[PDB]
Image 1 (cartoon, rainbow, N blue to C red):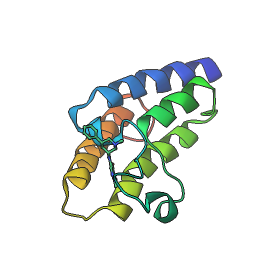
Image 2: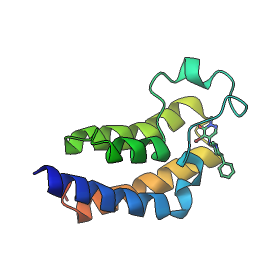
Image 3: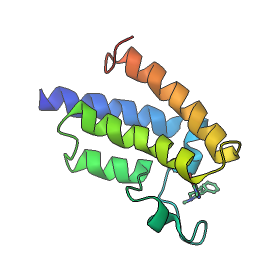
Image 4: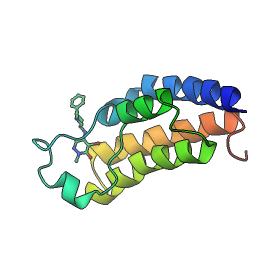
Length: 109
Ligand SMILES: CN1C[C@H](Nc2cnn(C)c(=O)c2Br)C[C@H](c2ccccc2)C1
């Protein structure tokens, strides 16, 4: 059901982008912030790119969406110190989006 999938993902992403811990991940990492980021992290992803992918019908499966979302967090944990503000935000956002994924029946409760 592509129409159910699209609206469900749109509604989920709107909530994720509204969370206070989403701020580090709203737009792509800039080279000024981390000059080697795009050599280290080979599949960079952020919530603006995910919005763009959603709206162009890239997410033809739930799993494609969940893979990008989980990679926002995984990239952050690979690049940044494990005890850092970005990693704290990643963990907070992760906790929230798993609650929402469960609420939406998009993973097992
Ligand atoms: C585009 N850029 C991404 C930053 N997030 C970053 C930066 N560098 N690295 C290495 C990261 O992992 C993340 Br997440 C957060 C920043 C910002 C966002 C809001 C307010 C102040 C700063 C806006």
